Image (cartoon, rainbow, N blue to C red):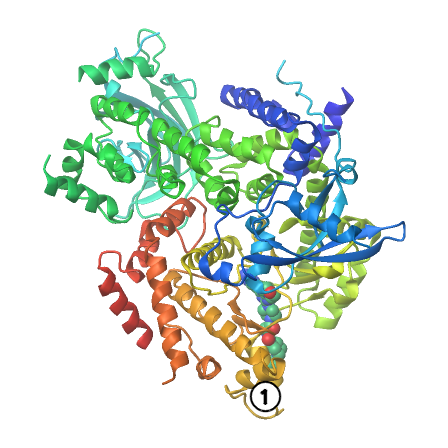
Amino acid sequence: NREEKILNREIGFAIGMPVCEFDMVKDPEVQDFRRNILNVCKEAVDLRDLNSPHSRAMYVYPPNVESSPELPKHIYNKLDKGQIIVVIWVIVSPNNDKQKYTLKINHDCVPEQVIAEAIRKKTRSYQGKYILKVCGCDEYFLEKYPLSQYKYIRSCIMLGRMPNLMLMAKESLYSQLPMDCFTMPSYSRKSLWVINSALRIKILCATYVNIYVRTGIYHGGEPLCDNVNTQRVPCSNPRWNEWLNYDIYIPDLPRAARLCLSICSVKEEHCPLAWGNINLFDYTDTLVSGKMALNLWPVPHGLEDLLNPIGVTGSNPNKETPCLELEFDWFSSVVKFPDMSVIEEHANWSLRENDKEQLKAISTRDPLSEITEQEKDFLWSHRHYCVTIPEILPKLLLSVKWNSRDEVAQMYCLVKDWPPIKPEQAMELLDCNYPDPMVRGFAVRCLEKYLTDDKLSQYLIQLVQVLKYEQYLDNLLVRFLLKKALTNQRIGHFFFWHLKSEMHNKTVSQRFGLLLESYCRACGMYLKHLNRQVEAMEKLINLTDILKQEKKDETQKVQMKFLVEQMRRPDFMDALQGFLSPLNPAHQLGNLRLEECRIMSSAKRPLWLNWENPDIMSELLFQNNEIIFKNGDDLRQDMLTLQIIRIMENIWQNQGLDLRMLPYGCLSIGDCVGLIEVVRNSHTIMQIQCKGGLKGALQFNSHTLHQWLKDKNKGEIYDAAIDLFTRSCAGYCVATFILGIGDRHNSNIMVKDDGQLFHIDFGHFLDVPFVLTQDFLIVISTKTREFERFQEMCYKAYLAIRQHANLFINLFSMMLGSGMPELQSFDDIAYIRKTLALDKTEQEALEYFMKQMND
Ligand SMILES: */C=C/C(=O)N1CCC(C(=O)NCC(=O)N2CCN(c3nc(-c4cnc(N)nc4C(F)F)nc(N4CCOCC4)n3)CC2)CC1
């Protein structure tokens, strides 16, 4: 049909590759995924069309709310007797005159009550036929949440700013909602464990080789038996035809067993050349048999062993690579993995107070803390009591002998009825350590039952990452993520972008490509806006690449002239004008203010772009939006660091210490190509010093910052600015120490006109003292009550963050999958286990941090 073809073209533009390439993939799992994934799209669409137009309006404009309605003590105290002052705006007449109405109302009021009191205050001079929009952006208060629970409202209460909302007729918004029509695509319409034998595989021959073959059987990262080296054969004739036998009975193979192979050379000096991984069982539970051709992958940098087990599974798309031919035993009939019923049958067939408290203390430990064989057998002998302390499930799982079908079946049974645990603890069961499908299903159930969409957006990147650890295209994790992304556009935006930002990686090009196909097919009208964003980023990448490639070594003004010339090309202006900000899709970006765009030139010619805000009430939020488009350096590290900083600020706020951090927006959109939010009214310390040097030929003294702030904050604003600086500074001190952020200096740090301090450009982390300039110490006031409160702040924040070491360590263990340089093995993560003194006690870690900050 016509709709099908147009949708195919748009989806191909959005994903990068055309839809027709997926059809030519003669892979049963690929077509089966493309077809079976559509049930999730159908569920999402039905949930959208369920409750008439309000359901769609909620799908497109979901509430940006905190997970808990309860306010911290200090946040509530900032309220006027538990109430908040709110300005509600109304546009009247065709001229659209803006009339404000100020109200003082209970912080826990529903938007309906707010609208009611607003109409009351307005008539002193309906029937719920209105809704509340945020003045200056496309965020809506469509749900009966308590106002204070909306992130915007809680932010206004924390910042002392006053919330400005616009009253808007509901019909005016529903008229702006397209009648979406998701069209179903055109591509939709035995022996068991009886084998009882040892596993053996024939390595046949290898092509495209320019030595021996090392192989092993693994369950996730652990080997189910010893590795087997084949006969060292000359590279001229890469023909082994050898048979490799392993110390593993065939039915003893767990469900997620994997064959990991690589080709090594010798000088003495063993060196890998090309690696590969194969699923012993396919997506239909069938045990693979017969001949099989696997194209290998190039080696990643800094590989310790001669094998890459943690690497993706599947044949290299580029078939012009090393190709290894293999042979698997073929028995009576097609072998399948047993049904859960046979598992339960074979499982049924197959205690002191001090010991229970020992189990509890074990569960308390952090993930990276190793467990001993004695402790493993101890947890296993007490596997049933561990159900009472559920958060020990990760270590219990780690204590299993996955090469024994008996223990595997009994653990399956224990999982089928295992109690649910917190999402922060359920994510630990999804990294590379736990490839078992039942464990991952339990974790996905925990997430589905106990994860708010706020917390989902807060951890969306880690989940998109752990997607790579999935044994098969079709699994419960991807279906959960896809349902949420197709029922919540705020989540689907960063879902799509986290996926697309890695389409360049042929390791996951297939998986993410198919997932993006399904999403774009079911996402609705937002595909047009995503396409406009993609074309804008395309033009920006073109301009940045061309800039350096052809004009790199010109002067600032000549590069500026060329940038103004090419940026004015109509095919370019149309592309970069009138679209949604990928950093925050609620932000419209209208026409470019070219007079305000420039090339920073600090590193790799970053672009500083400036758009007008076309919002009807842009002036009440910001009339201009600024973004740094950087094509050059990797921003994934920055994304993760800013996420962790936001989480630390959330912890501190919910624990009762107001250390205002600044986790500004940062989004990697492609191979080292990304965007960065621009914090208004912010300058680097080096900028302050240069502006305050007061001498063309003289150096720059430190005592300038306090003077600059006092100038920018005169009167009663002075103490407030000093407090803001001190608190934000203590927060960032503790953050940078714990995370081991790279070299700080006078331009890595920034301050705002009201005193807030923050950091930028997190080059390398996890590889130790703060700058603590005489500037900072003079702003705080060495021997004053101010510094006493400062040290108290720092110690309290260090303890608060030490209390969530499990969460932070799990976040890093999940990000391990992404090919980030400063994060390649658990050894890099151990730096946090160091700086937080996990193996020490509370008082011990307190003394440790005191001494570390004394230096
Ligand atoms: C002393 C005299 C002299 O020679 N000069 C006067 C001042 C000098 C100077 O200050 N140079 C540094 C500078 O002003 N800027 C560079 C940094 N930049 C900025 N960078 C980033 C960022 C973050 N993360 C990454 N990975 N990369 C970058 C960067 F490549 F863009 N982010 C920001 N923003 C600012 C707004 O809020 C959010 C963060 N800014 C600012 C300019 C120069 C001459």
Quarter residue 201 falls in: top left
Q: Position of residue 756 (x, y in %)?
A: 54, 70
- Label tally: 1
Locate the N terminus by quadrant.
top right
Q: Position of residue 624 (x, y in %)?
A: 73, 61
Q: Position of residue 235 (x, y in %)?
A: 36, 36
Instruction: For label 1, count other residues whose C-alpha is less than 10 Å away and answer few (under 14), some (14-19) or many (20+).
Output: some
Residue 367 vertical placement versus 436 (above, below): below
Residue 756 vertical placement versus 361 (above, below): below
Quarter residue 80 falls in: bottom right
Q: Residue furthest right?
A: 94
Residue 768 shown left or right of residue 611 in the figure: left
Q: Residue furthest front?
A: 124
Q: Position of residue 307 (x, y in %)?
A: 33, 40
Residue at numbered disc 1: 693
Q: Quadrant of ligand 1?
A: bottom right
Quarter residue 421 falls in: top left
Label 1 residue near ligand 1, CB within 8 Å: yes
Q: Nearer the viewer, residue 539 or 307?
A: 539
Q: Nearer the viewer, residue 58 or 437?
A: 58
Asked whether residue 629 is in view, the answer is no
Locate the C terminus by quadrant.
bottom left
Label 1 sits on a secondary structure element that is loop
* Residue pictured at 46% horizontal, 70% vertical: 727
Residue 335 shown left or right of residue 126 in the figure: left
Q: Nearer the viewer, residue 743 or 218?
A: 743
Q: Amino acid at mark 1?
A: Gly
Asked whether residue 821 is in view, the answer is yes
